[PDB]
Length: 316
Ligand SMILES: Cc1nc2ccccc2nc1-c1cc2nc(N3CC[C@@H](F)C3)cc(NC3CCOCC3)n2n1
Ligand SMILES: [Mg+2]
Ligand SMILES: [Zn+2]
Image (cartoon, rainbow, N blue to C red):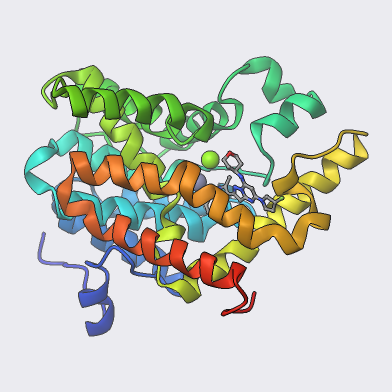
């Protein structure tokens, strides 16, 4: 029955193993790419193919047509997680491999392209339901809904308690994509690394490490080849500037990164974001998971490209 194996064209088969892989513009290939990544990083026995495929198409349908936080982002974040898991295969359990690829696919479900801040200022009903990590708690609740549709329980062969464990892996992974939580989590991990107290057999330490892997996967567009990184930056700002428009309509001055009038400062903004967020992220992750080195190196390469843009040597 494991006689039906998923295969990719030669170029994709080789390049999908590299951290900087780009899943391409053919969206009808992204489910196949995802299944392939599950079969190889988990095993062909991890899920029944018919439920997985039905689950994947329900997740796709509950992603929206927004510039950045869309289906392509979900698969892209999932692929970064595949590359981390394939280069660190000894360190993770069967449940974690299983749960972390799904958490990445589902992590921005039903994203409308607005920050937790905008939901709070707009007084969106979701803000009353969840006061912190508003969108992330909605993404997880959307994941549970889909898992609960008929013929969608991809975890049907797990015991009650294993099912509960993997849903807890998934819940914490999706919550950890709230960038507001990342600053505390990374400082804690850094302290624990440099004191030498960090212990991957400690469940609350695993939680923190997985959280950091989630942030690294979520930001992974800063770890692509420069043309990908630069084009993706247009999609991110298209959402930021629409949100800033929406802030102005509420009579609220938007923070600078969401103001389309500060367009010419995008190169300085990116430089800001690389030094304050991205570099520290991939540094701490490489310290803990040495084989994730190419993420840091490609980030450093793109930081150097943004500096190049600031000094007029490149155009954007
Ligand atoms: C938040 C994000 N998330 C990304 C995720 C993936 C890829 C790029 C991503 N870039 C950004 C990003 C983009 C950006 N542009 C800025 N500008 C532009 C022109 C001037 F107004 C300033 C300023 C910032 N400061 C950050 C620093 C960390 O605290 C929050 C704000 N950021 N941050
Ligand atoms: Mg998110
Ligand atoms: Zn995301």
